[PDB]
Image 1 (spheres, one colour):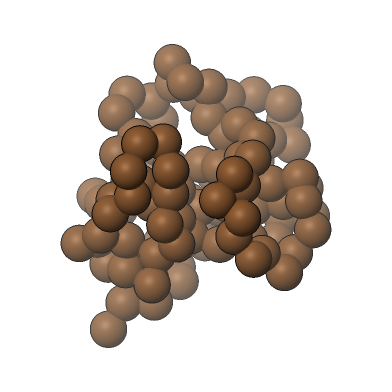
Image 2 (cartoon, one colour; image 1 turned 45 degrees about the vertical axis):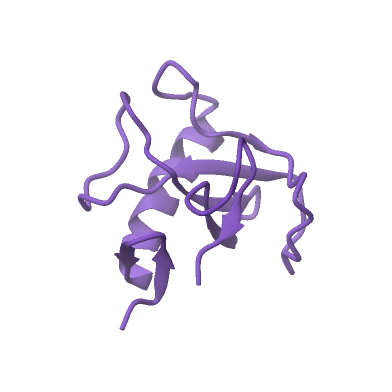
Amino acid sequence: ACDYTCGSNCYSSSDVSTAQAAGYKLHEDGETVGSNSYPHEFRNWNGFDFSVSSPYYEWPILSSGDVYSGGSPGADRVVFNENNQLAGVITHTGASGNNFVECT
C-alpha cells in the first residue's frame, strides 16, 4: 500500500523524496517559501524518536503530488536534517492543536 499514510493521504517513497529534495534545496540556499516561511526548524516537542541527527526542518508534502510553493500547506510534513537525511514523515491529522503524529 502506502509507504506513508498521513491521515487519508498515501505517499510513496518517491513522493517523500521529491518533497524532501525541494525543502532541502531551499534550506541549503537559505531561502523559504510561503507566509509561514518553509522550510523552518522543526522542534520535535512531541519527542519523536528520529535516528538521524538534529537540528530538524519541516517542509510540507502535498496530497496533490505537487511540490509546495506557497499558500495552504495542509497537515503533512517531511522532516529532514542538514545532512539531507530524512528524519520522518509527520502530520497534524489526528493530533490536537499544533501537535503532530507520525505518519504510518
